[PDB]
Image (cartoon, rainbow, N blue to C red; front, side):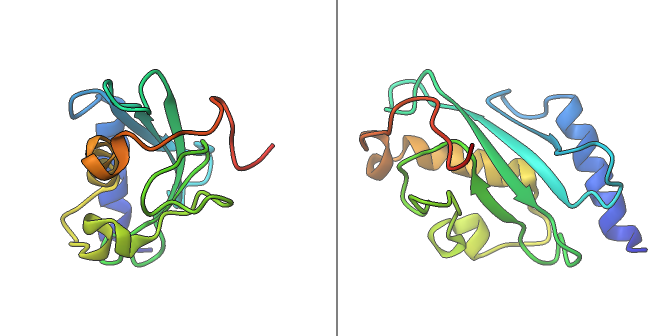
Amino acid sequence: VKVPRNFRLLEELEEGQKGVGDGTVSWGLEDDEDMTLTRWTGMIIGPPRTNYENRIYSLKVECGPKYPEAPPSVRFVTKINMNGINNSSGMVDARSIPVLAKWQNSYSIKVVLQELRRLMMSKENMKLPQPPEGQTYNN
């Protein structure tokens, strides 16, 4: 087993339970059963003063075998119009997101979500028209 990886992910799991950060993003395991700690769920409170306000975004984050040496994969479950996000799958294009494009082994799920929230408030995204609330790329 990958001790460094396993250890790091447990640290993140614990930080997600103590609400590290400003409380506007959260994360945890998707099924709390898989001890592989591969599939996580992310959450971002839409930033006030943007067209994302009053909405909560659900995302899926995957931390592969090479994590955290390699970046995790990310995708919105909640439909969103934002630079870097595919309009049919919700998949986040890593090269469109700095922390993913230039990933560093010191980053984390927390950092990815915090960066996504910052980008949400950025001039290029904050006034983008959004689809009807509650929509998801599935179900």
